[PDB]
Image: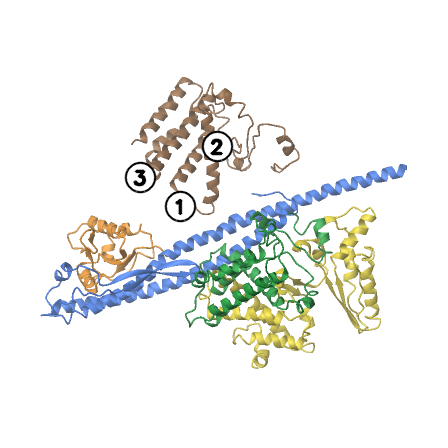
Chain colours: A brown, B green, C blue, D yellow, E orange
Amino acid sequence: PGGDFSDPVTSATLGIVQVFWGLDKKLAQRKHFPSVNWLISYSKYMRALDEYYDKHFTEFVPLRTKAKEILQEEEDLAEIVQLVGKASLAETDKITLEVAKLIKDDFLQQNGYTPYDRFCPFYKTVGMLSNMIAFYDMARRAVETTAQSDNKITWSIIREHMGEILYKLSSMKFKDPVKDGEAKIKADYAQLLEDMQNAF
Amino acid sequence: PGGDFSDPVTSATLGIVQVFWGLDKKLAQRKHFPSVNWLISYSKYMRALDEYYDKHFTEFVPLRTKAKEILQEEEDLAEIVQLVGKASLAETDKITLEVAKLIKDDFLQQNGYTPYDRFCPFYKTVGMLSNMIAFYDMARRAVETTAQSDNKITWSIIREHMGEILYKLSSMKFKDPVKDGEAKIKADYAQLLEDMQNAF
Amino acid sequence: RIEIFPSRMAQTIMKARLKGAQTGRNLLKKKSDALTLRFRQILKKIIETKMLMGEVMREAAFSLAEAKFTAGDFSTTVIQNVNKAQVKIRAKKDNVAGVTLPVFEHYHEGTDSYELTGLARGGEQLAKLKRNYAKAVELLVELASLQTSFVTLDEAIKITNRRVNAIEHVIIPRIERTLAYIITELDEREREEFYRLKKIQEKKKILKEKS
Amino acid sequence: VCLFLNLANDPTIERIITPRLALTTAEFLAYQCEKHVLVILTDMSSYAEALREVSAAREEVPGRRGFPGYMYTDLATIYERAGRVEGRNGSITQIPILTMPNDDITHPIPDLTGYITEGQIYVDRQLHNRQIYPPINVLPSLSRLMKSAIGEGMTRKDHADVSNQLYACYAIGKDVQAMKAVVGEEALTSDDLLYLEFLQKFERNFIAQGPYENRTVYETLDIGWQLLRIFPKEMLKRIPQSTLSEFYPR
Amino acid sequence: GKLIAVIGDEDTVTGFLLGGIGELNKNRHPNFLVVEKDTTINEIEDTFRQFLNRDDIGIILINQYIAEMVRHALDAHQRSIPAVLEIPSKEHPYDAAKDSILR
């Protein structure tokens, strides 16, 4: 009642169940579907599933450990922007807020009535997550290795030069089940553009 | 720790008892022992003890009236420094923030397992309090009457020059049970030491 | 946006958090008025002395013409012979409401590099053209002292004006709608205790009526 | 004095019959023997726990915060035994002294007496820890029938204006007292320095008076004019010139 | 910042060098720049970048007629040091450039 999770029905249920998909109303006041609040939600089959995950998708457990770190790093800095402002941030934090905004818009948002996002098989899930985190790790080396000395990459030159590549990252959700093997290739075909653009 | 003054056990008790030594949890988290905070604690046997205090320890009553003023003058100024900073503070105000900090570490702090602070007699209590407020009264005397014409120290040259004398005030809680005579004359020793410094 | 659980003790805690935030406005708003009042009076000192240096530099420019009428051309003698500076500045510090203001102070380590300029034709129009321009750099340092105080004040009164409004719009309404949640949730416990205690009294009359 | 004790040992049912006893004798001395009686009721917060205790003895269900629902009627039976009547020269006035729990005015003991009484006097812990007796702050305190009390025939003519000016300068002087902390002792002007020197003498000479000094209402206004004389003219805007011309030059 | 810099004009700098603000350390640069009729807009922009990056320069004097060309370069400079002033020319009187910071 009232969307409050301090309820004798809800709080009694959370002591019994293992998975909790907390739906947020503010994620429904904007059209962000599904509305699962990634901060308060949890699962308890983590240790029970990684024995399945080192057999079929052998790279996915290091991915969610960073993707959950990026989404919490955004929330710890979102309270700074509304009080202090966006102009006073560092460069390792402005790359954090924009990759996490790419995760919330491409990976987390999912239209249920469109013909392609009404069902997403798990190779498409691990596939499009493996490129949005490698892009986060590649943009880390552009800031951390060239740190202070040279007139370096400061991420303002990234967003104007990667405008074709960011449009590839924001369009990975459009892969219908009319292709199965080609979607795994285009996940790496988008990666080879991501491979070379950090060199140039 | 809880239901500070609105709790049926505590609220019914304070309408009956005369003395209330309120132990603070915040002083206990910073390991300030004893954790009796001086703002919400009270005693009501202050009119009944001035007949005893005008007979046996006649120095005491004008000191306890002033020592409670300095402890709140720091409290009303502690909320100033955490908002705007110490940089625009006055000089009659900075002489409160050092002596009140000298009160909270020398006078109010007391170790119950240390073999000399496990029981502090009342001549030792009136003794070290009469020096920490005479130090406050002489330093108030220096800054106020000599102001804006004479080149009098605005507390920055005092705090480094009294570094041996401020060590004598902070080490005054160490005399014991192995003296009473020596402990009494050392308070008069440290008082005549300060009378030469204020003659400068 | 709510913060913590209602206990009858959190209400006194949230009123203490509200009390510091209510006095976090007026203690910081009046700082933002003390900064703006000096910021507005420096701008009047900016505008007044900027039309005052325009008259001094006009007088120094007419002095220049006079010197050239008397004394040849010095547009290569003066330019070539510079080695060290005769007028220098040292940055001093000032403050208003704990905001450190950079300010400039001028001083002359005077070794005159134009001690002998002219000296055969002119040299009387010089050392009063020097006086007309050393008085000009006397004023242009004093104007630049107000320039560097003006430019660092509004970039330090913007960060104070944001800290006031972040309290007024983000922190104070969040505490106040937290405190409204403490009141209605504590009223909902009192009806639960009222319904339980009235039900006991209704059952106590049932056993009394049979017995 | 008709002093009525009631300790914490003697029964709690006797706390209910105690102000009914005290106001019965204060209705016989006032407008049955025709004299002015001042009734002091303390502690009026300790009355209501006696009212709460006999309520649960009758197996009655407690209302808001444990206190009974008829407490606004029960406080009305003893607060409204006051005032003065038509054909009788006596009167009766009440000062019911009560302590608010956890300094909360939203509590029903200082709230239900606020709907029915005519102004409040505040004893604060801010002035008490500053060693000021009596620790009464006058900014949130108010007397709703003080316009009627004072006047020309009643105390003297300047009472309505010296209290209006002493309240104004204390409010302004409290605001500049924080700017000495956060802005600077040098940045404040000469007039704001004068409000600083007013507040240091207002809290120590006007409010602080000691537990045995009986200042009359004429000695009170003379101390109030000494603290207004430190200000020059044309700042005392609450006092008209018809009374400011006499009392200021002295 | 201990030096005063001047970009000025031809008649402007020879009055200010007579004031005593010129200084030549032969390693780094001269602290002034005479701007004549046949110098490009780029050369004014490099020396403006020189004086802003130099540590000893605390004040930058410049005529506003010369500052009208490098106006895009000095509208981006929003620091407290070095101060930049616009002084009037022999021909060109006055008004613009700091009130962009305050309208």
Asked if disc 2 and disc 3 are in contact, CB closer than 8 Å, the reply is: no
Label 2 and label 3: CA atoms lie apart by 29 Å
- Left or right, D187 with reference to D16: left
D151 relative to D70, above or below: below
Q: Residue at x 63, y 28 (%)?
A: A16
The chain containing the residue under callout 1 comes to A
Mark 3: few, some, or many residues within 10 Å (few <14, many ≥20)? few
Q: Secondary structure at mark 2?
A: helix
In the rendering, which numbered label is found on residue C149?
none
Q: Is residue D123 visible?
A: yes
Do discs 2 and 3 belong to a common subunit? yes
Q: Secondary structure at mark 1?
A: loop
Mark 2: few, some, or many residues within 10 Å (few <14, many ≥20)? few
From the viewer's side, name the closer residue of B30 and B2.
Answer: B30
Where residue A75 appears, x then y in whole percent? 48, 39
> Label 1 belongs to which residue?
A87
Do discs 2 and 1 belong to a common subunit? yes
Label 2 and label 1: CA atoms lie apart by 25 Å
Location of the C terminus of chain A by quadrant is: top left
Q: Residue furthest left?
A: C120
Do discs 3 and 1 belong to a common subunit? yes
Label 3 and label 1: CA atoms lie apart by 19 Å
Q: Residue furthest front?
A: B178
The first of marks 2 and 3 along the sequence is 2
The first of marks 2 and 1 along the sequence is 2
Q: Residue at x 38, y 59 (%)?
A: C101
Asked if disc 2 and disc 1 are in contact, CB closer than 8 Å, the reply is: no
> Label 3 belongs to which residue?
A152
In the rendering, which numbered label is found on residue A68?
2
Where residue D197 appears, x then y in whole percent? 53, 70
The chain containing the residue under callout 3 comes to A
